[PDB]
Image (tube, rainbow over all chains, first blue to last red):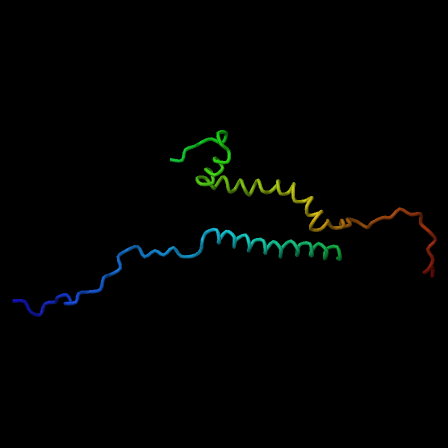
Length: 61
Length: 76
């Protein structure tokens, strides 16, 4: 006979995940490049104007 | 394999080819070549379009060229 030992469910189990769970997250790489140039150029607009500002302050001193 | 076509067979194809295979050379070289070429061409435009230069900073006491006039006041 066979009683008391463990058995699978009569409905079975759910199917498991065995694949590569790899979402290609993020943006397009060109978006990273264009955002890079945007952050850069805005920084340069803050930088060089402040430098010319400092040069006029140097003149004033 | 990505051995070589040669620069002197087709230029623009070889530029694309180096950009696909050796960007360590070509994207240092592009930043390098964009320096002086833009330095040559853009600086007439900024004086023409954006804004002209600054007045030069004085480096010492500026000396005018005059003849020591009679200047009164504060004798005693």
